Length: 264
Length: 13
Ligand SMILES: *c1ccc([N+](=O)[O-])cc1C(=O)Nc1ccc(C#N)cn1
Ligand SMILES: [K+]
Figure 1 (spheres, each protein chain N blue to C red):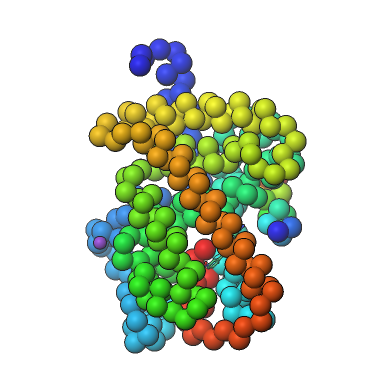
Figure 2 (figure 1 turned 135 degrees about the vertical axis):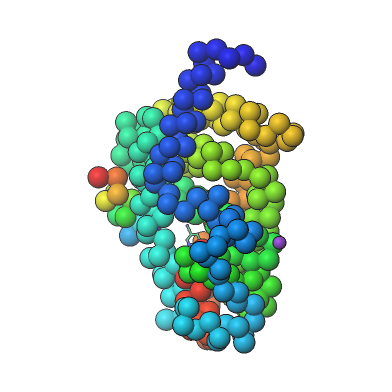
């Protein structure tokens, strides 16, 4: 490795992406970790860990599963708008065919939402209600089927992903690499997409080498996490298909339905 | 989801 015009350009690209990341996403990983580790004075989230604590936190706030998925997708509109705004800052993205821009984003947003969801998770549970609540992992897992199976694969991804100890500067480039995936179905001009991702991948590799001296093959390990993200998305699409094809009267507490709407 | 594509299209404007 040498400090040459090429490496300096890749550092400028990483800094540009980081600055747009900060402007586009008001809730960063650093802010989420500060809440989870009990270092935010102004924020002491209420902990929901069983049915008793669920009903005690009531004031702090068609199949049931479909309404949850409709509700959380509606609450995820802001995230989609922010991810879309971030993509405009990726050099070359707006010059692509508009159909390809929509295709890259319509598949990419789900993977990025799960990436950001992992920042809200530790081994014990996940932040909800704009950092004002904390829903434990085992309470979610204990809920009746199919609801008890919704979040557990995402916690399993989150613990492996968070063990990489990426920061917001790492995540900014990683998210850009997700968006510029030239293997999405329906893409018209794959080559200009791959040319941009090649630059983002070079910027990502250099960023990880400089920022994580104690990691081995972190570049490869991070890319393998895209395989986990796509598996999570595919499982949801499959579960919705079988839910659309199975008629099951599913009862769930309205407070739990509201909480699931803050998840994904 | 067409609603999602529409959200993305309006945001891209
Ligand atoms: C919304 C709220 C809660 C859950 N959950 O507990 O699993 C899921 C959703 C949701 O709509 N998830 C989701 C994942 C992937 C795609 C796609 N494509 C759409 N929706
Ligand atoms: K812990």
